[PDB]
Length: 36
Length: 36
Ligand SMILES: *[C@@H]1O[C@H](CO)[C@@H](O[C@@H]2O[C@H](CO)[C@@H](O)[C@H](O)[C@H]2NC(C)=O)[C@H](O)[C@H]1NC(C)=O
Ligand SMILES: *[C@@H]1O[C@H](CO)[C@@H](O)[C@H](O)[C@H]1NC(C)=O
Image 1 (cartoon, rainbow over the protein chains, first blue to last red):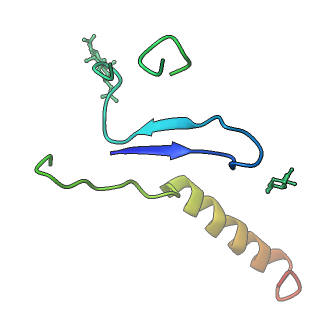
Image 2 (cartoon, rainbow over the protein chains, first blue to last red):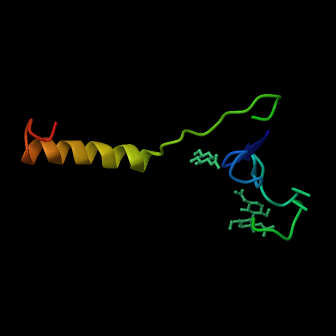
């Protein structure tokens, strides 16, 4: 499963994605490059 | 354990609970009923 963390629509439009029950070696703008 | 269903992890780990219990127990040793 995938979940999204957001601080609210009114304040910002930036979210953080959380992939549940997966080890970060086959996850692949959110593919790579950003902070993992 | 991967068959179509998942098990989510608890929010508070064991150390969290142990530290709460130690705090309560030290409080009841030193203060008594006052800290309640
Ligand atoms: C995610 O996968 C990587 C790679 O398979 C795991 O890295 C291994 O870590 C152990 C413990 O340090 C080493 O003995 C292995 O040699 C590592 N693998 C490789 C290919 O070098 C990593 O532990 C995995 N993460 C989780 C949480 O399971
Ligand atoms: C947006 O919502 C948050 C809710 O935590 C509130 O604190 C903030 O004042 C709101 N801002 C505006 C501009 O509505």
